[PDB]
Image (spheres, rainbow, N blue to C red):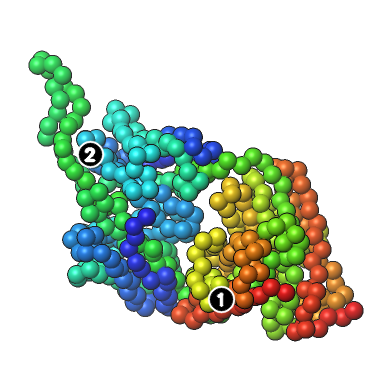
Amino acid sequence: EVQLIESGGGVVQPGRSLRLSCGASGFSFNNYGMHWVRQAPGKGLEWVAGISFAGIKKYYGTSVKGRFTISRDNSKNNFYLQMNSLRVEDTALYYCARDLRELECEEWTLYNYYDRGPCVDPRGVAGSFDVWGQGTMVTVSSASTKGPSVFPLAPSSKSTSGGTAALGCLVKDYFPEPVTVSWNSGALTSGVHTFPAVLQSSGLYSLSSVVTVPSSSLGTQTYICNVNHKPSNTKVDKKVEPKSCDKGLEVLF
Amino acid sequence: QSVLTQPPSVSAAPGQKVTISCSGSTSKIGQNSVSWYQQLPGTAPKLLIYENDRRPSGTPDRFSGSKSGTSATLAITGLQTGDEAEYYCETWDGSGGVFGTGTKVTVLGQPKANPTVTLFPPSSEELQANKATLVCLISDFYPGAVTVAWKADSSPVKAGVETTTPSKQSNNKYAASSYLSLTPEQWKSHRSYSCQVTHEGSTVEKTVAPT
């Protein structure tokens, strides 16, 4: 069974370096080229680098050329990406992928005139990727553990529609993941949705938790969002009240 | 990050036929072959088409490709539920490695739902922290694909934006979020900011201003 498996991923500070390792199996590794394709989740696919089956030709994307480096060890069915001078914008899920073009070497190095050595075929990749690995995650942040600042997404006339009001909590600037949010100690679960976290250029995560409720209840019912960040050992409780100065929304009391 | 342009999303009912388009520079697609990949949600991509119109031993007759000039096209007949994914076009131009944006193909499994867009201004509390963040929340919509865009006094904004991809809700519909990070100066020194959400050709636009 054909398999590609990556490894080396993890959280790493910018400026530093990191080596990923792709292990190939289920086919003749020394007959195919290899590529690294990354994907900022879920911003789409970006091609990083590629190597010819003999290891003679190296290709690099404009975003990484000069900083990153590729190589392969056919004796180990391995395939490496040496990342240097890491940038916060290098954060992505890194896939290793096999090159489409199957080639048989037709030019080796004979290290002594009695016998063999590395293949040296000058060719030559196709540029199409017919096998993919599971991908290994590479997060780049200079941040250490930090607790969140919780801000209210107050309900207003611009969040109500059809007798259903929308309110939430902005959980800003924390690290690392995760952050679990609840509403009224878990009494309120209907209409609640907590969105995926967002990694800012600052190096910190942010997310929002929103809940939908009867617009008429805003004047009597009380809504507290319960943010929880165990990494920094923090529990914030923010009471969200309707927008202060809003004509377009009537509220009891 | 040089890139080939694709449509954001297309959708059709089980059994119908879809067409997806690529397009780009002549020094890229004008002179080189094109490939197509399928990326089911949560898993790695998978080659569907190579050399413009060749199918690998393992992809059905249903998928087909065709290139002409500076444009390329992927087509899927007899849609099955398991065809729901993102589709990327790609080309190799020597140094090579150029993907599409690309396109999500949704196979409708429920009634289309229009998004309820809610835009929040920065809290005075946050402004006291000499910072500002506009939070645009998109809720209750299907198919689960959108395109958010921010504007300042009806002028495009690109820097300081981060958008999450749509995620399933408890009611099996989708929701998404977008954040525009400002300084309190920018926030107050503009007449209005607006969050423009596009969903199935339709575009909703909410607006907010200082106090």
What chain is tagged by disc 1? B
* Residue A66 image position (x, y, % from top left): 35, 39
The residue furthest right is A253
Which residue does the numbered mark 1 point to in the structure image? B153
- Of the two numbered discs 1 and 2 in the rendering, the one whose residue sits closer to the viewer: 1
Q: Amino acid at mark 1?
A: Asp
The answer to whether residue B116 of the structure is visible from this angle is no
- Residue at the image point whose x is 47% and y is 43% from the top: A87
Residue B211 vs A250, above or below: the answer is: above
Which residue does the numbered mark 2 point to in the structure image? A57
- Residue at the image point whose x is 76% and y is 47% from the top: A234
Quadrant housing the N terminus of chain A: top left
Secondary element at tag 2:
loop
Q: CA distance from mark 1 to mark 2?
A: 50 Å
* Residue A150 image position (x, y, % from top left): 74, 57
Q: Nearer the viewer, residue B28 or B32?
A: B28
> Quick check: A188 left or right of B56?
right
As drawn, the label of residue A16 is none
> Quick check: A111 left or right of A34?
left
> Quick check: B74 left or right of A234?
left
Q: Nearer the viewer, residue B25 or B199?
A: B25
* Residue A131 image position (x, y, % from top left): 33, 48
Quadrant housing the C terminus of chain A: bottom right
Name the quadrant containing residue A183. bottom right
What chain is tagged by disc 2? A
Q: Nearer the viewer, residue A247 or B178?
A: A247
Residues packed near mark 1 inside 10 Å, few (<14), some (14 to 19) or many (20 plus): few
The answer to whether residue A90 of the structure is visible from this angle is yes
Q: Amino acid at mark 2?
A: Lys
- Residue at the image point whose x is 35% and y is 36% from the top: A69
Name the quadrant containing residue A108. top left
